[PDB]
Length: 139
Length: 138
Ligand SMILES: [Ca+2]
Ligand SMILES: [Ca+2]
Ligand SMILES: [Ca+2]
Ligand SMILES: [Ca+2]
Ligand SMILES: [Ca+2]
Ligand SMILES: [Ca+2]
Ligand SMILES: [Ca+2]
Ligand SMILES: [Ca+2]
Image (spheres, rainbow over the protein chains, first blue to last red):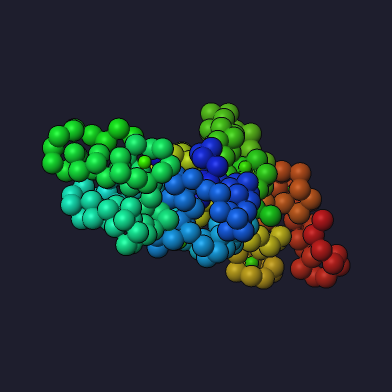
């Protein structure tokens, strides 16, 4: 499960989560799972606006946000429309071929073997899943 | 500062906060300030619904709530209308006299000496505050 804002993965939202995101925005260091947790506003990309929303939440000053909620994801569902199908395959293929970069927040769903790399193995697994040759993704 | 759901007052919302509130609902023990923090849904009373909302939040399953937000308190402003006047005084007097009980969440605003009791001392102190004899409630 991915908890929005829970950058260190410990299940609770704290100033350490914020510190890790702030450091990442200076020098990238977050895993795919952390990038999914870091996309506080849900627009797919991890940036200083996400950081700001997390700051306002932690200081008690925030409006309504998804911080603390479990993020809805399905492995292989890269566009997060609730189905794994050939449009998900296209997104990962273009990513691998250099003709379209996956959003920061969708890398976790694309990483079908959970090794924090997007490569041919992920594509093949999604291909097998779509065509019914495997019942689930290994992750 | 009162932060909603932050029962232990450490500035963050965690499983410890839930444990303290659950313990209180079994055997009452929260301070007035903790009661203010525990009224998650803002309805004035601290009960199992507040606990349930905190539980859902900590499991990542909650809807929209005020958990984590600061709730601004003005000492002596019992009706939360932004001024301290005779109407706040009446609310504390009735409470003391047993002719109307303050909500759990307003006890912190009424407690002029911070001893987690509302008694004749809180009445005298708000009187002095309203009439300007004391510059601020202790
Ligand atoms: Ca955390
Ligand atoms: Ca974002
Ligand atoms: Ca899809
Ligand atoms: Ca992979
Ligand atoms: Ca706390
Ligand atoms: Ca309540
Ligand atoms: Ca008032
Ligand atoms: Ca008192």
